[PDB]
Image 1 (cartoon, rainbow, N blue to C red):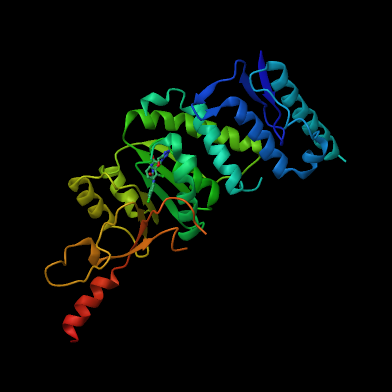
Image 2 (image 1 turned 30 degrees about the vertical axis):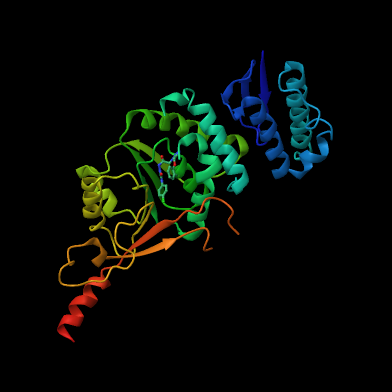
Length: 314
Ligand SMILES: O=C(Cn1nnnc1COc1ccccc1Cl)NNC(=O)Nc1ccc(Cl)cc1
């Protein structure tokens, strides 16, 4: 006893066992099935016409026969459209949130072990989407998320941008191990829907290691949730940022330098002498979520050059 969903692009079908799994108090595989069908009907208007009107209205999630009739009415509609077609784009924001939730639900089987990953789609997703729209990224950029956890920020950026590569680095054992499954599941679900993503790597490691010193120096876009970082972690990170190229950017949860930094003879060693800092917020740019702010730092050594020029030409 199981339920099968045919891929809109001919990939291997989605197979769910019966009884259907329960993910948490606010997610179960039954609603995942219904929402997957609905998203595929939105991205394929012909499928909407083939699909009978009543099917996605009159349903019982606690009835095998009911859930099978629903799955079959979608599969028969996929088959009809696939026949009509006889005679890979980026996902929409809406579809991506659903894909990430799907990937998470299938990857983190014991959620007890872990703004937590559970609520990523309900809080963090929209802020990250807002960050992707603000920090414009090209095919020349290299993206790194320092302390990537289960890897959802990396998967979101990689599905939205055209960076050469996207990296996620996590030191902790439990999230780094879950990231391995998230990676496999993300690639599997993206192929299922027939969606394109940029290249990405989720790896285990310490971003303060010698290996990561040259790697940070060659990154053009760093995303770092530094809210909980200690003084030594913060001080070492600033040391790594100081080797970055002009125009290199760091997007963080707490600024690394004062927003009002004014260079003088007593603060010449501060990171503020080689970077610009701006507070950005979805409330500044029609937002209705949390009143949050993120901080954009841009490597600019002219701050330091101008100070010296002013001393020589007063
Ligand atoms: O584990 C992860 C992402 N993650 N994956 N699954 N769940 C989560 C929890 O997310 C969050 C937790 C707290 C705050 C925000 C998020 Cl998004 N690390 N990466 C990461 O926080 N990036 C990041 C976030 C904000 C800025 Cl300003 C700069 C970088």
